[PDB]
Amino acid sequence: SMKTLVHVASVEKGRSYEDFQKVYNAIALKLREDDEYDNYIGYGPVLVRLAWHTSGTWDKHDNTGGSYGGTYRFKKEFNDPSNAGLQNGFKFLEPIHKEFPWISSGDLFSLGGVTAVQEMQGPKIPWRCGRVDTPEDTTPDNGRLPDADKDADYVRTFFQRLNMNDREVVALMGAHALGKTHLKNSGYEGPFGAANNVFTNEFYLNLLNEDWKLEKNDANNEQWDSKSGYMMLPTDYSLIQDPKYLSIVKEYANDQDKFFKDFSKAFEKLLENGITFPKDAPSPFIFKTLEEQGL
Ligand code: HEM
């Protein structure tokens, strides 16, 4: 591999907590307003998916990809087959960026995910500013995001590239409490769980408690379906097939607070992988929800 690239965080000129809380608020207000999307699930889940896809390209071996450069705005990454459907999240963020043109693309994509998690009643995610747009030729090639038709050994190896351990993997996957698979996007179809747009630990409870059947969907792909009408990907279900993952699933199924704390740590880490924060950078921001502000 090549010598690691160095990506030093640089605060948008003159900006501070209050500026980023205003961007958060605009995202949160649009989440509330544009609530018809995807049969009234709203844009929360796709924004969290967008944050994972734009951060999940990172390669610890050469520090390519990751959230820093905001490269999803370029054709090669925008048109990654793995990114099908994310254009809806990008379009959601367009008026936000128009109102706050000074925020970097990487800061906006990652802050979109933080805002969505918190506004869906998830844990506070501390968030740092200072990602800087990088040129088109820094865009990572397609193929760095994970396949869903795979087992636990694949999941474990894949996430080593993001410097995630077993606990971080199981915690991050809890985001599949949110939203659904869409046959036209991914070859999988159905809601993951019951609430769809409230962040809870129901991913782990459903894995353990539902009666899952391995079925074939209308795209001829196998997926796990329950009589409650939920589905899980093969990679999701692998978390109760592998004995080490299963232990952690049981822990989170039995401790909502522990899941929230571990998810918040692993999600912040995901959004910050590859970034060098200078010694005198601002501390991470913890944004108030609209509810906490009375807005
Ligand atoms: C092995 C790892 C993962 C695999 C294979 C995977 C795969 C998928 C697939 C196939 C979909 C359906 C997309 C569609 O049809 O619209 C999806 C949706 C989603 N993913 Fe994952 N994912 C993984 C990890 C993650 C992580 C780590 C996060 C966030 C921390 C995340 C957040 C989401 C969300 C919120 C959705 C719902 C999107 C929507 O409703 O539009 N995923 N994932």
Image (cartoon, helix red, strand yellow):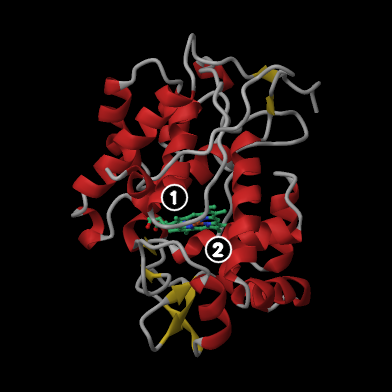
Which residue occupies 32% across, 58% down? 184
Residue 118, labelled with which disc? 1
Which residue occupies 54% across, 79% down? 205
Instruction: Tally the numbered discs.
Output: 2
Q: Alpha-carbon distance for marks 1 and 2?
A: 14 Å
Q: Quadrant of residue 253?
A: bottom right
Q: Is mark 1 in CB contact (under 8 Å) with mark 2?
A: no
Q: Quadrant of the C terminus?
A: top left
Q: Quadrant of residue 282?
A: top right
Other-residue count near label 1 (Cα within 10 Å), few / some / many at <14 / 14–19 / ≥20:
many
Above or below 136: residue 83: below
Q: Where does the image place residue 123, in percent across and percent down from the top left? A: 52, 54
Is 169 left, or right, of 293 in this rendering? right
Looking at numbered disc 1 in the image, what kind of residue is underneath it?
Gln
Residue 174, labelled with which disc? 2
Closest to the observer: 30 or 234?
30
Looking at numbered disc 2 in the image, what kind of residue is underneath it?
Gly
User: Does the residue tagged 2 have its C-beta within 8 Å of any atom of ligand 1?
Assistant: yes
